């Protein structure tokens, strides 16, 4: 056949590219970073009405000051989350402090290209790249609030706002026009709630969508359904307002 | 300290006319404390008999090991193991643990099913085979057993006679050993049948 | 470096055949004929010494090998494969038996050991099956005389008489005609020589034929005396001269 | 060293001394002998400072990891067994630690677990560890009641350490108090034994044998 | 042809080529441009940072390996992290064990040898990134160009990445000029920005878009980004 | 060492174990239960080295429960004891052996008979009407050798033990803080909460 | 590299089937037929020897019936050599169990273990599976007489009567036709021979082409006894049952 | 030694070996689970490609991981055993170290992890199995029902089915299961389960087995009669119209 870490004639790694495709098929995830916190929202997208929506966990906590959202083959994200939680906790044990959001992200991205059938560079025992992208958001004293997009390629970009998943090209275009350096946390919330509604196949309600944020004061929190439902109602009103 | 003097016990085997006998006491103690008066030290796999003195846990482990090995042997060879062969299996199994040996004193007894010839053999803890024609002793009262046997023994005794001889050897030797006694059992073996008799002795 | 062939090279085809075993058997088919016959008091195995050149010294190449003092082997197929199989067999007779029980293994068990070695070359990663079929003849106290055949698959079966290789079909047929359960060793040797003649194209004498027997104990071949229970090997390769003497009464 | 921890109606009282010695040398009179695993768990340190400090801080990291993984507060039983099993892995290596793992969970209520480097893990109501333990036990055993008030309980612990600080040459410095409630532990100050002794003597009338 | 001889680095084509290696080199060309040039007192790295969206950051392209050494990358970022990390260890080793700063020429040899191993064995893949190493050691200022093929060359200046050829011709021209910008970092840096803008086309170098790094005689390898590079735009 | 006693009567096995846990100069606990239920009809008592004691007991418990789930069946007492003997006989020749002695009392539902097994840390196993570990046997065996009868009722067994515990509380130098008694029979394992004065 | 020559013995077909297992089963279907019939007072194992000659030594032969334990035996259908590899490990597992618990291994536990080993070659390792199917006839004190079957996939099931190898469809239909819960060993012995007799691809069904074994609990004893019939014994029972 | 990447990505972003693993599940006998207000019921259908089996010994479809949790599945039988064993082992280890039995979600997340892992490790193919895991968290009375698949993904359901014709039976459940009023009885819950299976089992008294799980390790499997009784009362519900 062909090696799992082979280069295409264009200078790209097949498996990594094909990986990005699976990610495109995943549920939408959006992140907005403001000077008042970072918001992270996702599309639950249950496959049947019998599936209990709240058992869908696409937004998880890394540490009190770091949380993340996922899009793609979600099962592939578990070992990534584990590695992240361990990395942040370990850092605290060694340095009696919080791990910087960038550092935590870089650690996760280090697993990324550790795949192959015997690549001469160490002992990368993992048959294929991860099939899921991650939005890592957090806060730290040196660079305040931050949003990162970690891909199976091993590269991670910092964004003021970013969307990954099925409705990303569309949603990202929206974020391009909506984002500005002075958004309030509440604005970002509605804004994320709004874009999700535009790209989601289903009609967005507090059961097929979920919000969350991370603030320096209270850290990472996942908004419960009641809290979001109200924010949803508030959006419908401001939209019908003009 | 001495793994061979913790539990106590003895075993003795003798050859007679077209027969062999193997006997042992039934004591199992923890130094001065008597713990069991039913710890038999004789086992058999087919028509081959094995007595074992020494550290009780090893006596138990070795029996379990030889059962295991003689079982597979039967399944592959499609016949029961013979005295001479088992003796070699015992030897090599013990030597395999040359630098971390089982603290035991094995004794093999039986009659070759094809030649009818009687057979007994002893081993040190690391497998050295002692193949005597007369008798073999083992245990905390082995010195006494050597004395008893050397005097009481004579060649070609009949089954009924060898029984008396081996029993008197075992009995009087055990009574001069603090760690032996509390019961005894004697096996009289012939080509066709094997009788097992429990003896009556002091219980102190 | 490092053998990275950790997967089987012999696998099942849709028809359920195991290709490499089949091909190996085909290689056996092209090999020089060899045979074995069991008598009431012995066994004989024989083959043809197909000298690959007149400059070659046929004696320096034995197709009939002693595995234990009471067991011998002969084959048909790839000579180099046979040679290593004999080395491995002689060693396994020791490591898995003599060093444990203090005596040589009985024919069926040693055969079983060889068979296992062959079966593994049929499933282990990175290898091909052995391209040979062996005929092993031996004797042991509780089983008497026996003759076995071991094929590339690792399968083995007991025979009264049989042949393998080039003219196996013809030879097997000729054997079925002359074999009975009352043959004496000499009779089997005779029948063996006749059977082998039909398979030989050119010269047929004690220098072109290789033949051994599993029979009585040869105390003269022990090398020492003093131990009553040690009487000598039962395996004995016949000499060029010994064969010719019997060819005259052909 | 003298450390104690006891269970009662209002939760758990934890009191320790703060002296560090190497032979007859007093290395410190202001050492911390209580590790704040996290806001709900406390650990006492007796024996080797490095060993206790290191593994109890590590315990903290393992508890945190548990709560992230199970989205639920770790039980005192479970936290104590993590330490216990770690320590048991090193049995024979020379670790030296006598410790009390204390917490208040909804599921268990007030819970104290004694854990030492021999691998021993014991659940109990009252525990005293250290070269001053016997002194503290004397005071504790005769005044302990399950229905003690949080105020009196705190004092009993403080007094028990005081008794030990006085008689045990390897105990003293100051007393560190802690009250453990289901909502977390509450620090109750650092009481210099020096001043505490004279004060207690006068107000209580005890320590009559000492001239003040 | 090619298709049958490009499935892995362990295969030579009928003409003696190594396609996987060549495909790797392709990843560099697709990378943002970066430039390097040195006088006799300093060495400079000017790199164009590329952004994903206008809501994204401009990926860092310069990495410090020690106080006297550093590099710029073009291609797979992860591979530069690995290679620079290895360079960091090698510099660290030289210091700890021999109390000696690692020679820039020696670093080059070490990078070449690490890259070569990934082009002769089954299973691995060549590194897909180009590197420009600058540093001041016991023999002055230095600039090196590293190619995934394992080829490392010492130069006065150069550029790698998309449209790199612009800056490269400019430098090959300005040579006699900048090679003498001794004792004046600002002049060397400006010359670097002038070479890099020779590869622009899309936009123009902005504040959060330009990245510069310098090292020399009495200047520990330091990196300037944003406001700090404003005085060069 | 602690007190580990066992007596097999007509239809049950009774195990008595001291409640004290002493660490050096002080008795840290006087309510310790030195036992683990291996299965509904099998109980194991233990005494020995500080940490090894419980770690071993719980390790054995885990394995039996796992076997019970996998096979949806309860291993016979004899089976559970051979498993335990082997575990200790392995340990005796390892880097750091388990210094634990145990008594295994179980009711064989298939044979409908109680069984008592004594196994020391070396993997020495024996089946007895009654047994003990440590010094305990020294003070009690003469009493059991005297009053023991194969047809004793559970009530008679408890009276014979009480006698043993009294002798122990008289001649033994240490205060083991009384014992916890448990009965194992056809209906399972139950604890005699009233022995502090039975 | 090597990848080029890897058959990939452990992957799924687009239909979710395991190529190798399927092909191995196909291989097994050309193997001599083996029958297993469980009665109220025993179990019967019978097998047809594939390929034979006048010169084949039958007294010293065994290619289908193997003793695993003193209470368990198996009938083989497939590659003999592969079977022997599995049989030996099965024998070792039985003894390990015995030494650990001092009780003979329950029949299902041994079967599940052997099947688990087979299942392994199905999910990892890159090796061909064993071209073997077993019929297990054994007895234990928890379920008494039991009859099991395991194939290349690693699946196993219990039966009152069953067959493996060639013409199993024909054999199964005939068995399902005349089997009765209250059968007796002697009845089953007869059913077995009749079934093989009608499914043979050979002319007649003679003794030299059969192997026979029974696991009974000899009333005059109280223990379990396995009996691997000898040439002459098969020849006899072959006449009695009316097949001469 | 063998570490070939069997589960890799294809151009369209799919992992065929995992995809084909699902196909093996579709082929397996149907399985269903529905949770009542105070229990969970697991139903499985029995094949009939061959019938002359010994039901006493032939491996049952519902397995107990611990005394309070059960696991059923659809797919390769040989594969399910590996998962069941690992799950049973992890159940004991959890009790040994946390001194508390596993929650149903925990046990599920474990099994799922093993599955996910087999989708990106060299030399191994994914599990051709999908599972339904049900039970009651220690000291809790709220019923739990989870489902896992080859990919390693898992989630909880009010009711769910897997295996052949699961498409059919799921529909039945989607228009016969009200989250507002879940089968408030062990009886009416078992009935709804039997009804859902009859949509695909086609008259199979001996082809339908049910297991009822109640709080506090109360688990029991119904007998042919008990079930057959439910079938009977159901065929009448139809005829009576
Ligand atoms: C008490 O246990 C003690 C302390 O020094 C020590 C210090 C900090 C935390 C752990 C406890 N340990 C010792 O080894 C000395 C000598 C006697 O006891 C100490 C005072």
Image: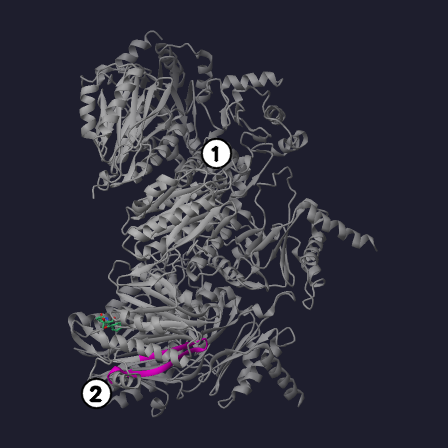
Q: Is residue A11 visible?
A: no
- In the rendered image, the quadrant that contains the C terminus of chain G is top right
Q: Position of residue G10 (x, y in %)?
A: 48, 48
Residue denoted by label 2: E182
- Region of the chain picked out in magenta, as a range: D176-194
Q: Quadrant of ligand 1?
A: bottom left
Q: CA distance from mark 1 to mark 2?
A: 83 Å
Figure check: A42 above or below G219: below
Q: Nearer the viewer, residue G36 or F12?
A: F12
In the image, taking residue H143 as reference, residue A218 lies left or right, namely left
Q: Position of residue H86 (x, y in %)?
A: 47, 53
Tag 2 subunit = E
Q: Have a look at marks 1 and 2 and say if they share a chain.
A: no
In the image, taking residue H47 as reference, residue A67 lies left or right, namely left
Q: Residues within 10 Å of mark 2 (few under 14, many from 20)?
A: some
Q: Nearer the viewer, residue G15 or B54?
A: B54
């Amino acid at each position: 056949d062909r090696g799992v870490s082979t280069f295409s004639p264009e200078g790209r790694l097949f498996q990594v590219e094909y990986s990005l495709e699976a990610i495109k098929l995943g549920s939408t995830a959006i992140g907005i970073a403001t000077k008042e916190g970072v918001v992270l929202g996702v599309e639950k997208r249950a496959t049947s009405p019998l599936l209990e929506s709240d058992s869908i966990e696409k937004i998880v906590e890394i540490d009190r000051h770091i949380g993340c959202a996922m899009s793609g083959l979600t099962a592939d994200a578990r070992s990534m989350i584990e590695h992240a939680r361990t990395a942040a906790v370990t850092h605290n044990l060694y340095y009696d402090e919080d791990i910087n959001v960038e550092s935590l992200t870089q650690s996760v991205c280090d697993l990324a290209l550790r795949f192959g059938e015997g690549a001469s560079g160490e002992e990368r025992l993992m048959s294929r790249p991860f099939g899921v992208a991650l939005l890592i958001a957090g806060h730290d004293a040196d660079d305040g609030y931050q949003l990162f997009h970690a891909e199976p390629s091993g590269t991670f970009y910092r964004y003021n706002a970013k969307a990954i998943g099925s409705g990303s090209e569309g949603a990202q275009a929206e974020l391009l026009n909506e984002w500005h350096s002075s958004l309030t946390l509440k604005e970002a919330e509605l804004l994320v709630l709004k874009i999700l509604k535009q790209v989601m196949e289903e009609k967005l309600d507090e059961n097929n969508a979920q919000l969350s944020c991370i603030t320096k004061q209270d850290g990472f929190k996942i908004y419960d359904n009641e809290k979001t439902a109200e924010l949803i109602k508030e959006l419908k009103e401001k939209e019908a307002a003009e | 300290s001495d793994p061979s003097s913790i539990n106590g016990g003895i075993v003795v085997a003798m050859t007679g006319k077209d027969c062999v006998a193997i006997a042992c006491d039934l004591r199992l103690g923890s130094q001065s404390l008597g713990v069991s008066n039913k710890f038999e030290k004789i086992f058999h796999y087919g028509h081959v008999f094995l007595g074992i003195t020494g550290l009780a846990t090893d006596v138990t482990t070795l029996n379990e090991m030889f059962r295991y090995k003689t079982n597979l042997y039967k399944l592959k060879e499609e016949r029961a193991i013979e005295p001479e062969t088992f003796t070699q299996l015992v030897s090599s199994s013990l030597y395999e643990r040359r630098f971390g040996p089982y603290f035991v004193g094995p004794v093999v007894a039986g009659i070759n099913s094809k030649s009818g010839k009687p057979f007994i053999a002893g081993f040190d803890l690391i497998g050295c085979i002692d193949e005597a024609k007369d008798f073999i002793v083992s245990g905390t009262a082995s010195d006494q057993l050597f004395g008893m046997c050397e005097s009481l023994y004579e060649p070609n005794l009949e089954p009924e006679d060898l029984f008396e001889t081996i029993s008197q050897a075992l009995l009087n030797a055990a009574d001069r050993d603090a760690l032996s006694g509390w019961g005894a059992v004697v096996y009289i073996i012939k080509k066709d049948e094997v009788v097992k008799r429990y003896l009556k002795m002091r219980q102190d | 470096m490092t053998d990275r062939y950790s997967f089987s090279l012999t696998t099942f085809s849709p028809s359920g055949k195991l290709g490499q075993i089949d091909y190996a058997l085909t290689a056996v088919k092209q090999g020089v004929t060899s045979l074995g016959i069991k008598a009431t008091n012995g066994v004989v195995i024989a083959t043809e010494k197909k000298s690959s050149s007149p400059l070659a010294m046929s004696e320096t190449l034995s197709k009939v090998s002693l595995l234990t003092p009471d067991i011998g082997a002969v084959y048909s197929g790839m000579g180099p494969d046979y040679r290593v199989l004999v080395d491995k067999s002689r060693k396994v007779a020791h490591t898995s038996y003599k060093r444990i029980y203090g005596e040589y293994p009985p024919t069926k068990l040693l055969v079983s050991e060889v068979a296992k070695i062959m079966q593994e070359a049929t499933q282990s990663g990175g290898v091909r099956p052995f391209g040979v079929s062996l005929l092993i003849a031996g004797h042991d106290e509780f089983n008497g005389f026996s003759l076995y055949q071991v094929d590339p698959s690792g399968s083995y079966f007991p025979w009264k008489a049989t042949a393998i290789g080039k003219g196996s079909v013809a030879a097997k047929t000729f054997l079925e005609k002359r074999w009975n359960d009352e043959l004496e060793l000499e009779d089997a040797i005779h029948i063996a020589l006749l059977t082998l003649k039909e398979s030989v194209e050119g010269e047929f004498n004690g220098d072109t034929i290789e033949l051994a027997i599993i029979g009585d104990e040869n105390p003269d071949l022990l090398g020492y005396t003093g131990i009553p229970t040690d009487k000598g090997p039962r395996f004995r390769k016949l000499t060029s001269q010994e064969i010719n003497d019997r060819l005259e009464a052909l | 060293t003298t450390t104690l921890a006891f269970r009662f109606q209002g939760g758990i009282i934890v009191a320790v001394d703060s002296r560090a010695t190497a032979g007859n040398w007093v290395a410190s009179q202001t050492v911390k002998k209580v590790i704040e695993i996290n806001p709900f768990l406390l650990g006492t340190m007796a024996g080797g400072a490095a060993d206790c400090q290191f593994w109890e801080t590590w315990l903290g990291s393992q508890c945190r990891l548990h709560e992230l993984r199970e989205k639920e507060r770790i039980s005192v039983a479970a936290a104590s067994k993590i330490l216990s099993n770690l320590v048991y892995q090193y049995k024979g290596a020379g670790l030296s630690m006598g410790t009390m793992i204390c917490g208040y969970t909804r599921k268990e209520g007030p819970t104290i677990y004694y854990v030492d480097s021999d691998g021993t893990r014991l659940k109990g109501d009252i525990f005293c560890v250290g070269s001053g333990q016997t002194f503290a036990y004397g005071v504790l055993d005769s005044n302990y009641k399950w229905d003690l008030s949080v105020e009196d309980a705190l004092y009993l612990g403080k007094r028990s350490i005081l008794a030990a600080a006085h008689r045990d040459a390897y105990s003293g410095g100051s007393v560190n108090l802690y009250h453990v409630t289901e909502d977390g532990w509450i620090y109750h100050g650092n009481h210099d034994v020096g001043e505490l002794f004279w004060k207690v003597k006068e107000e209580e009338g005890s320590f009559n044998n000492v001239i003040g | 042809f090619r298709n049958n001889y490009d499935g892995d680095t362990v295969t030579f084509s009928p003409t003696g080529r190594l396609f996987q290696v060549e495909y790797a080199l392709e990843a560099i060309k697709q990378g943002s441009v970066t430039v390097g040039l040195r006088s006799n007192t300093h060495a400079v790295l000017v790199a164009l940072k590329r952004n994903a969206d206008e809501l994204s950051s401009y990926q860092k392209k310069i990495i410090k390996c020690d106080e006297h050494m550093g590099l710029s990358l073009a291609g797979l970022a992860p591979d530069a992290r690995v290679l620079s990390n290895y360079l960091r260890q090698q510099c660290n080793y030289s210091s700890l064990v021999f109390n000696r700063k690692l020679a820039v020429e020696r670093a080059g040899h070490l990078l070449c040898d690490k890259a070569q191993k990934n082009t002769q064995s089954y299973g691995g893949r060549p590194y897909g990134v180009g590197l420009l190493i600058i540093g001041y050691d016991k023999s002055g200022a230095h600039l090196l160009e590293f190619q995934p093929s394992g080829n490392v060359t010492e130069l006065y200046g150069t550029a790698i990445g998309a449209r790199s050829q612009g800056a490269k011709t400019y430098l090959e021209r300005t040579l006699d000029t900048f090679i003498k910008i001794d004792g004046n970092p600002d002049e060397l840096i400006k010359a670097g920005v002038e070479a890099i803008s020779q590869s622009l086309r899309d936009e123009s170098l902005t504040v959060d878009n330009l990245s510069i790094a310098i090292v020399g005689k009495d200047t520990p390898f330091t990196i300037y980004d944003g406001e700090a590079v404003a005085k060069y735009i | 060492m602690d007190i580990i006693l066992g007596i097999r009567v007509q239809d049950s096995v009774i195990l008595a174990s001291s409640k004290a846990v002493t660490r050096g100069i002080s008795v840290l606990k006087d309510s310790d239960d030195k036992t683990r239920q291996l299965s509904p009809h099998t109980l194991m008592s233990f005494a020995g080295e500080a940490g090894d004691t419980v770690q071993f007991a719980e390790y054995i418990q885990a394995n039996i429960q796992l076997y019970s789930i996998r096979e949806d069946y309860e291993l016979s007492p004899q089976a559970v004891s051979s498993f335990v003997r082997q575990e200790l006989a392995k340990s005796i020749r390892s880097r750091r052996p388990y210094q634990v002695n145990v008594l295994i009392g179980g009711y064989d539902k298939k044979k409908n008979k109680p069984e008592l097994y004594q196994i020391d840390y070396l993997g020495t196993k024996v089946e007895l009407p009654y047994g003990a570990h440590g010094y305990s046997g020294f003070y009690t065996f003469s009493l059991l050798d005297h009053h023991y009868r194969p047809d004793m009722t559970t009530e008679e067994g408890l009276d014979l033990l009480k006698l043993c515990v009294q002798e122990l509380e008289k001649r033994m130098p240490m205060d083991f803080k009384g014992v916890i008694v448990k009965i194992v029979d056809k209906d399972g394992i139950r604890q005699v909460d009233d022995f502090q004065a039975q | 590299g090597s990848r080029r020559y890897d058959s990939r013995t452990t992957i799924f077909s687009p239909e979710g089937r395991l190529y190798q297992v399927e092909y191995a089963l196909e291989s097994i279907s050309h193997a001599g037929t083996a029958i297993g019939i469980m009665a109220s007072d025993g179990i019967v194992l019978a097998a047809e020897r594939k390929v034979t000659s006048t010169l084949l030594e039958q007294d010293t032969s065994t290619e289908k019936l193997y003793k695993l334990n003193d209470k368990i035996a198996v009938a083989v259908a497939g590659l003999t050599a592969d079977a022997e590899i599995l049989i030996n490990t099965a024998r070792i597992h039985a003894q390990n169990y015995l030494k650990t618990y001092n009780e003979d291994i329950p029949v299902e536990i041994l079967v599940r273990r052997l099947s688990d080993i087979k299942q392994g070659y199905t999910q990892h390792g890159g090796l061909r599976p064993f071209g073997v199917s077993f019929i297990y006839a054994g007895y234990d004190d928890r379920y008494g007489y039991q009859l099991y079957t395991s194939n290349p996939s690693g699946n196993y099931t219990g039966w009152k009567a069953i067959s493996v190898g060639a013409n199993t469809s024909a054999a199964q239909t005939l068995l399902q036709m005349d089997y009765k819960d209250d059968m007796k060993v002697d009845d089953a012995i007869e059913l077995a021979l009749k079934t093989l007799s009608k499914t043979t691809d050979s002319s007649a069904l003679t003794y030299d082409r059969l192997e026979f074994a029974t696991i009974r609990k000899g009333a005059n004893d109280g223990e379990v006894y396995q009996k691997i019939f000898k040439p002459q014994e098969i020849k006899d029972i072959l006449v009695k049952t009316g097949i001469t | 030694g063998y570490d070939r990447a069997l589960s890799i990505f294809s151009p369209d972003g799919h992992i065929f070996q995992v995809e084909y693993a699902l196909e093996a599940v579709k082929r397996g006998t149907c399985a269903v689970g529905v949770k009542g207000k105070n229990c969970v019921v697991l139903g499985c259908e029995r094949r009939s490609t061959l019938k002359l089996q010994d039901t006493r010994i032939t491996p049952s479809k519902v397995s107990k991981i611990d005394s309070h949790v059960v696991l059923s599945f659809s797919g390769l039988n040989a594969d399910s055993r590996i998962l069941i064993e690992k799950a049973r082992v992890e159940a004991q280890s959890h009790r040994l170290t946390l001194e508390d039995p596993v929650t149903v979600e925990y046990l599920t997340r474990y099994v799922a992890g093993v599955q996910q892992r087999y989708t990106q490790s060299g030399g191994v193919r994914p599990f051709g199995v999908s599972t339904l895991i049900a039970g009651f968290d220690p000291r809790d009375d709220e019923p739990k029902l989870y489902q896992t698949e080859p990919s390693g993904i898992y989630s909880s359901w009010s009711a769910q089915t897997i295996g052949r014709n699961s498409k059919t039976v799921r529909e039945f459940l989607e228009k016969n299961y009200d989250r507002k009023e879940p089968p408030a009885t062990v009886e009416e819950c078992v009935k709804l389960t039997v009804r859902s299976l009859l949509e695909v089992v086609q008259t199979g008294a001996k082809n339908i087995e049910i297991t009822v799980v109640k709080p506090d390790s109360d688990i029991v499997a119904l007998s042919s009669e008990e079930i057959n009784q439910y079938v009977t009362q159901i065929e009448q519900e139809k005829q009576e119209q």
